[PDB]
Image (cartoon, rainbow, N blue to C red):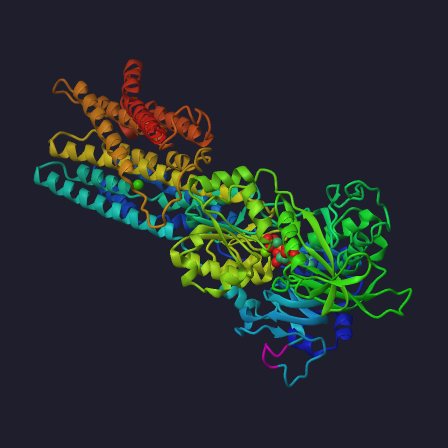
Amino acid sequence: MIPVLTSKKASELPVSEVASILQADLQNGLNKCEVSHRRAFHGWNEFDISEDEPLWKKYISQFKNPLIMLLLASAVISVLMHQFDDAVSITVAILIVVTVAFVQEYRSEKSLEELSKLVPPECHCVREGKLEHTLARDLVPGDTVCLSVGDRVPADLRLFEAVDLSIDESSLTGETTPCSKVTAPQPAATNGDLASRSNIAFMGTLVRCGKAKGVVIGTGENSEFGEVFKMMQAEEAPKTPLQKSMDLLGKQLSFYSFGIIGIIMLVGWLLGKDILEMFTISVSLAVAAIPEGLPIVVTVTLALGVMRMVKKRAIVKKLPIVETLGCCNVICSDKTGTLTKNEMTVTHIFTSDGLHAEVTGVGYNQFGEVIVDGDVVHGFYNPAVSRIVEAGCVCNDAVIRNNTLMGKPTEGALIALAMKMGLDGLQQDYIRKAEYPFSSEQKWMAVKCVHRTQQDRPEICFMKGAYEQVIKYCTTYQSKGQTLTLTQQQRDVYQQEKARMGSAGLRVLALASGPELGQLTFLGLVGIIDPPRTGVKEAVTTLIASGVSIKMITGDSQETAVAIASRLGLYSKTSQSVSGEEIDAMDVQQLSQIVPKVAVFYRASPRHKMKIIKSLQKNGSVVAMTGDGVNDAVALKAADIGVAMGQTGTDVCKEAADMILVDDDFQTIMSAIEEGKGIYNNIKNFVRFQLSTSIAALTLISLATLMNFPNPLNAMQILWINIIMDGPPAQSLGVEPVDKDVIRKPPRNWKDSILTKNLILKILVSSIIIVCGTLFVFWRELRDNVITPRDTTMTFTCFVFFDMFNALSSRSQTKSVFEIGLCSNRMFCYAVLGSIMGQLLVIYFPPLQKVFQTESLSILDLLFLLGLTSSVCIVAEIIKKVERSREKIQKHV
Ligand SMILES: Nc1ncnc2c1ncn2[C@@H]1O[C@H](COP(=O)(O)OP(=O)(O)CP(=O)(O)O)[C@@H](O)[C@H]1O
Ligand SMILES: [Ca+2]
Ligand SMILES: [Mg+2]
């Protein structure tokens, strides 16, 4: 039986003894069958998840509300009296109400737990001698885990290989300085504090630099500080500010409703009316007017938006970011990953002498050739191009195999061009001795390699990079084999050629070589191509046209970036560009007045990205920046809508950013805006419908009380109307697919409220129309002195039909009834049908007849009510149509 090794003992114990105890193969990894056995015995590589879900507890918690308690008290006091039919009716009504509330809460909790836990932790592991790609959830104590830069440590590792490792342990230790890691055993005297353990990698820490490979010593709860981990991250309350605003609005509406109910009670009691019946009616109205489904529906619509985002490759965490996601003003993205595909090929070759050579072929394939202006070259014919491809081979770091690329796209394109000429065998012929790492701030890499067949000649350097960083280190050039020196008369024409290459759609680079890396010989430039991704130009145009001001932050040259922006809709006739030196000269103040006028940035850095973020946030704008680097993590954290990458993004940037895309494309941002605006529109629909229904009911009750005639609503019918107003139909209205025409609207403001003048006017119009219809029904209904329950049933049916028709036309503030389709959201149709059958059963069920005192009606009366109750829908449709037509005509003219 394998024992679990503690962190301190693993640090104390030698690596070989540790591997002996865990029976782990450091080279070939661990086999799958033993992986399954260890997983079965030790559980999975997860945190022990346990919580109380005693459904009877949440059933009881649905009770104890003051409204339900008062209803139960009224039921008890009626039981104490001589009446029992009212008591049984009220208790079955409150039972239906609490069951509806229970299913609403259950659905809300269900959506809550389908939310989150959607980005599993993923890390490398060695099994059966192969580096295989598993989730961290699959780990067992004994596997060999490879750690890379930017990867999050999945479990406690006993490090045995490490070259210049720095691990950010600020999360678990609080030290802002990453801790260097070693592999030697640690002394017992220094094994006291956590930070002194320099040979163990802890789960949840981020690797900042270096390479590593260790064996898991702990999984799940046995891991050190796992206790404090489940202490902090297990429970949290990240309340969305939109939820707070909705709660405040609901509380204000509830206070106003309570004031209205109190005024109505005072007026009725001062007028000498009923006591118990009026009290029950008032308490039913109070429980009706309270918006209780608003938080449930907002959680449901947030979860639905997140799920719809995920269904089409848009993973969004950090729930309250979605609320401000729709209020997007400025969008920034790179140019190699999000706008154009990462498929680079070289189609132009330029040398020191000057010969326009064109290269054909698309992709990393060997079908292709180099075409000078009339020649046939398949070998050592032109010395300049041969030297260029040889330098490309020497400076190359990646390796191409079976038409596959594993490395940076630029080196892949260079090696593909080299293989096209037939010199693929020179990549491994030269062996590097001194290596110069390539960096964003450096923009050039150098190698020191010599031929192995002969070593009489001294060392020769081969380096490539940007032209601005190449001509500075190069003052010699070749014409016909011999070495000469360049002057200004060649630098100017080289600059013109660089600009010409940067035009159209080509990328500009430079090749240099020499004996010592202080004086080289210029070779020429390579015309790497970069085709834009399909369906990006129209997306960019339709984004910038409406309300967005997308900018460009790319590391290319001036001409290349300008041409790429001109191909899309980013560049205009009034836009400028800021260089890296210029953006470094000014920190915040001088950059503020120029950021809204520049859409293309020169070769920048993560520090420059931070500067742009600070300048944009100073002006008061929302920025959505996408990054794929370790040093872009701070930029993503500072940005409110920072986006990470799935395939080209590290784990550090994945965790730091609030949005992760499994595919790099400039199409999910419009999708983010569309779902955000759609869920906002659904919330507006719910709010408008609930407010209109509540206002109509309260106005009808107030007019009934003030005019001194019995109210044709009772209490059970009021409870049914309440269930309709915030229940299955209200949630059906809240659940709605995103409208196609929702992107042609200026971005929303974060400080804007939910109630507008148009919404208030529509609510008032609908309420007054419903009230007028009910008054007309009553006037045509009571033409004598005899009052029957049939009249009350007819009034209740008219009110139900009016509410249903209002909900029918409340699913679109701008679209018509037939524009979205009669059957688009099947949930709404199902709810309407269920309400219809429930009303019919209430009318025609002897038990429900006794409960609801509905008596009976006729087919002709029902048809007349249906014909009359359609007034709200037609009026709303015509006013919406005329308003939309007038707005479109005015904006067109
Ligand atoms: N393998 C390589 N060797 C030498 N230079 C390289 C290189 N890859 C890129 N460069 C140089 O680095 C410069 C800027 O590159 P950087 O990596 O900062 O951004 P980038 O090339 O990835 C474009 P972007 O950031 O918009 O995706 C380019 O002009 C290029 O000349
Ligand atoms: Ca209510
Ligand atoms: Mg970049």
Magenta stretch: includes residue 194? yes
- What is the quadrant of residue 372 in the picture? top right
364 left or right of 501 in image? right
Residue found at the far top of this picture: 860
User: Residue at 84% of width from left, 45% of height from top?
Assistant: 377
x, y percent for residue 869: 28, 22
- What is the quadrant of residue 177 in the picture? bottom right
Residue 212: tell me if it is visible.
yes
Residue found at the far front of this picture: 489
- Give 367 or 707, whichever is nearer the viewer: 367
Magenta stretch: includes residue 81? no
- Give 666 or 82, whichever is nearer the viewer: 666
- Give 37 or 418, whichever is nearer the viewer: 418
628 left or right of 290 in image? right
378 left or right of 212 in image? right
x, y percent for residue 158: 70, 71
420 left or right of 593 in image? right
Residue 47: tell me if it is visible.
no
Tell me: residue 363, above or below residue 724.
below
Residue found at the far bottom of this picture: 189
User: Residue at 15% of width from left, 32% of height from top?
Assistant: 703
Quadrant in which the C terminus appears? top left
Tell me: residue 615, above or below residue 502.
below
**Which residues are the magenta region?**
192-197
Chief SS of the magenta region: loop
User: Residue at 48% of width from left, 47% of height from top?
Assistant: 550
x, y percent for residue 524: 72, 55
Tell me: residue 84, above or below residue 2.
above
Quadrant in which the N terminus appears? bottom right
Residue found at the far right of this picture: 453
